[PDB]
Length: 138
Picture 1 (tube, rainbow, N blue to C red):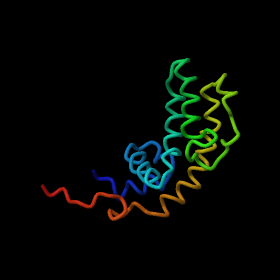
Picture 2 (cartoon, one colour):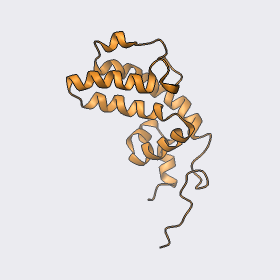
Picture 3 (cartoon, rainbow, N blue to C red):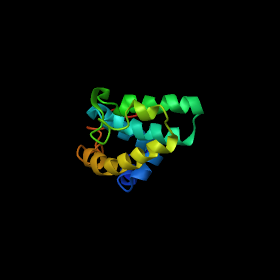
Picture 4 (cartoon, rainbow, N blue to C red):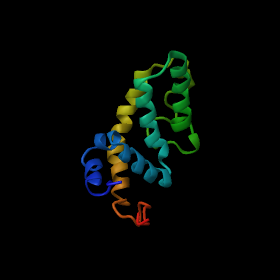
């Protein structure tokens, strides 16, 4: 893996680069993951993939799925955004894909602000933070 120099420049260039480059989504997830915000990173991925492909019934069950897992009223955490008393199952009884893209664009904005202030808080630019440690050697 050559991901160190240019890679960090990529993701700290634009959030799109991060959410485009596989290694970005990988290493960035691990960060929030261990800091307990994987709900955030997975939410965007899920709603975007949900936006790109899904059958009708599946989509509806996935609508309530992503809501219940990442947002919900508690979700054993949830990201601190519009969600607590928002949506509610009452709208999941008639859910549509693009309706989440509203929250997606929202979390995208919050993501840049917050998630940058997180990733650039504990810079994984160091191997002593991003766990590689060992050499390839043999």
